[PDB]
Image (spheres, rainbow, N blue to C red):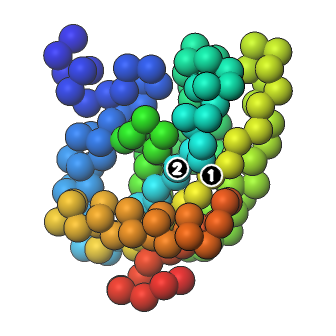
Amino acid sequence: KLEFLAFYDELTGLPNKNSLIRWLNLKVSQMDCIDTYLIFLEVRDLEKLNVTYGYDLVDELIIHISKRIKDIAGEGNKAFKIGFDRFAIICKSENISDFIERMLSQLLLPYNVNGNLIRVNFNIGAAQIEAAANLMRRCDLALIKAKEEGLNEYVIFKPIEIQ
């Protein structure tokens, strides 16, 4: 279909960056985005993995990752695949840091991909939702700040200031 090609990710089935944008413009229209956050998760050293395990194995890994993200995310929250090695989440949460850590601790858990026990690293950039581009840019910056900090570290931007 032309709609699935325009809004979803082939390999993962998750909605892509275009879908993230529509839903972002929507979310920003409302009254109170009751502490709703945009979160950017990056799978680290995914290239070295394509080299080490081959592309087919790694695409399977990505699927595994997407499902886990989709799982600890929840149904009331949205998960997207916006880059080869990057995912995005829209989530409403009173305590977003713990939400981030809970998920990170779980993402850090091994993946049994076709008998292959695999462990990967991540980084997370998050931003208080409050146009679409500027928010995504803000998340991007947080992700950058997080990687400078090191592997498996996260940064949350609030109206901005480091958190």
Instruction: Point out residue 46 in the picture as x, y percentages from the top left corner.
Output: 57, 37
Q: Is residue 55 left or right of residue 33?
A: right
Q: Quadrant of residue 55?
A: top right
Q: Which mark is residue 76?
A: none
Q: Is residue 1 left or right of residue 123?
A: left
Residue under the image location 48 percent in, 64 percent down: 143
Q: Is residue 77 visible?
A: no
| Secondary structure of residue under mark 2 | strand
Q: Nearer the viewer, residue 124 or 39?
A: 124
Number of other residues with Cα within 10 Å of mark 2, as a class: few under 14, some 14 to 19, many 20 or more: many
Residue under the image location 42 percent in, 88 percent down: 161
For residue 15, above or below residue 31: above
Q: Nearer the viewer, residue 3 or 141?
A: 141
For residue 115, above or below residue 152: above
Number of other residues with Cα within 10 Å of mark 1, as a class: few under 14, some 14 to 19, many 20 or more: many
Residue under the image location 58 percent in, 14 percent down: 56
Instruction: Name the residue that disc number 1 marks.
Output: 122
Q: Is residue 18 visible?
A: yes
Q: Is residue 82 left or right of residue 59?
A: left
Give the spatial CA distance, label 2 vs label 1.
Answer: 5 Å
| Residue type beneath disc 1 | Phe
Instruction: Point out residue 66 in the picture as x, y percentages from the top left corner.
Output: 55, 34
**Proximity of marks 2 and 1: CB atoms separated by less than 8 Å:** yes
Counting the numbered discs, the total is 2
Instruction: Point out residue 2 in the picture as x, y percentages from the top left corner.
Output: 17, 16
Instruction: Name the residue that disc number 2 marks.
Output: 42
- Say whether disc 2 or disc 1 marks the residue closer to the N-terminus: 2
| Secondary structure of residue under mark 1 | strand
Residue under the image location 61 percent in, 72 percent down: 149
| Residue type beneath disc 2 | Glu
